[PDB]
Amino acid sequence: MNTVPFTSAPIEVTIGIDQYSFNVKENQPFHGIKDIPIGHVHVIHFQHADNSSMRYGYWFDCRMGNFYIQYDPKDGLYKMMEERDGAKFENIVHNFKERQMMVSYPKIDEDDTWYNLTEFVQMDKIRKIVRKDENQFSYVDSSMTTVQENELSDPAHSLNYTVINFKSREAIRPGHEMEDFLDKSYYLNTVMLQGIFKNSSNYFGELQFAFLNAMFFGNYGSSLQWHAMIELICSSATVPKHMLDKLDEILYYQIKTLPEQYSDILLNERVWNICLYSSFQKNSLHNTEKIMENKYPELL
Amino acid sequence: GAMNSSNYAELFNNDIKLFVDDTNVYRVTVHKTFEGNVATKAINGCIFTLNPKTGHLFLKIIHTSVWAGQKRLSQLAKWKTAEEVSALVRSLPKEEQPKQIIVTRKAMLDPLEVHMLDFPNIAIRPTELRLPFSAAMSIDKLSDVVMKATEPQMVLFNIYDDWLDRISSYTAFSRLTLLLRALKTNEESAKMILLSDPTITIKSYHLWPSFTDEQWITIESQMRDLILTEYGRKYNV
């Protein structure tokens, strides 16, 4: 089990780690998060007590180095940093544990929620979407735009999501305007899966990365990407049986995990009514249909 | 986006534009089967593509052969319309190509957008106007060429005859719509008004009678009356 230590907590902030969250008071003696499960990506995220605008955070994998958080009072945010000196880091970490100024990643043993939300997300892929290759961890926030949004505005700080556009020549074969636009199977299976993502795993990795950015940072652009990647499978008459079964499972946990009071802004009435009720896959998402109907019947 | 009465003069400026009306693309007679069920029998249709400035009507005759062994035909018809508009655009020299195409029905926005992905400098626009282009098959010479067609085919008409030699587009378009609105409200009365004087003939290459300026006014007056009569009767008002 791994640990992300904090130098200090100089400003009052709500700290998140994956689906968990802790209030830290201004200059509370907080020195980080311990017992972080090895084997998955994690996200540590921040909302300042004062400016509840700009939620921000850091995607990391503890296998890829020793990471800590330090408040920067010039730039006014909690910064993730790599400690290259390993012995200095063991030493920093063991002190704070003995003094018990660290909260423990609070994992219920029966609970597989995080695995289920990050199953296909891999740090190698996150770093291609968020390009800053001199760090082994990726900074995301609420206001960061997507490469697509930037088309329709600083390229360094974009989210580089795979562009998906139902009304593009990428999506529409010359001579199959009607076939390709009402059954998006070629766009899904040949252009995106065979062509760009290579396999279903990488496709689901980006879908899941996009949802979590939508949920944890209310990143509008990530919400659109999640919806777009859901609509492309739902509007494809031809999809492998396993992708539908895994999609049903992916959506189930994302719908289950959503805060009850954010359906208004994170869920797109049209895409869901279409996926669940009108699309080719109206009868392929039993689990997602059941939870959506029982938990958000207002939307449909 | 959409076109209304606030930006009406746009239709008569010098950007090449066409209206597309697909109402008459897919036409069926509904009939009884021997077993007492219902069946449709498709009859030839046409795409109404009109340049409102020049009066050029690119009338694409949709022959019943295009529907043979096809499913979900009212949906195919929107896409067959989009294919045909695309092809006509592609067959025209660059300087003849429209800067805008205005669809009279919103269900054509996507089928046409998708067929014109190659023409991203052509704006596909809906309208909030209630244009009477559905009544184009009440024009005798247009109904004849459509019903007689044994194959797909396309006839350049000029739906303003020689009017532009005496009047502006604005006025010609208003006269056209006033006649189509009449024909659509009461085809019988509308057409009785147009041919009650045998002395006034239709030129071979024309659609409408050769009316003098005075005769148009008297025809235009008679057409406005007809449209109120039928409204006060539709509604009892």
Image: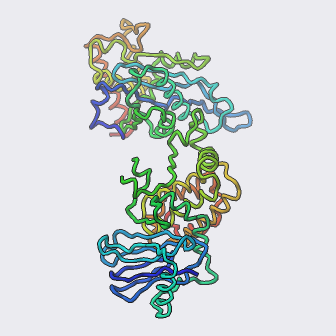
In the picture shown, does residue A163 fall above or below B100? below
Quadrant the C terminus of chain B occupies: top left
In the picture shown, does residue B55 fall above or below A151? above
**Does residue A300 show up?**
no
Residue A237 x/y as whole percent: 65, 48
Residue A169 x/y as whole percent: 52, 39
Quadrant the N terminus of chain B occupies: top left
Is A54 left or right of A280, judged from the image as shown?
left
Indicate the quadrant where residue A204 lies: bottom right
How many marks on residues? 0
Indicate the quadrant where residue A9 lies: bottom left
**Does residue A277 show up?**
yes
Residue placed most toward the observer, A181 or B68: A181
> What residue is drawn where x is 49% and y is 16%?
B155
Residue B18 x/y as whole percent: 40, 27
Q: Residue furthest right?
A: B35
Residue placed most toward the observer, B189 or B54: B54
Residue placed most toward the observer, B85 or A76: A76
> What residue is drawn where x is 54% and y is 19%?
B146
> What residue is drawn where x is 41% and y is 24%?
B97
> What residue is drawn where x is 55% and y is 25%?
B45
Residue A61 x/y as whole percent: 54, 71
Is A196 left or right of A31, judged from the image as shown?
right
Residue placed most toward the observer, A277 or A145: A145
Is A242 left or right of B99, judged from the image as shown?
right
Is A253 left or right of B109, judged from the image as shown?
right
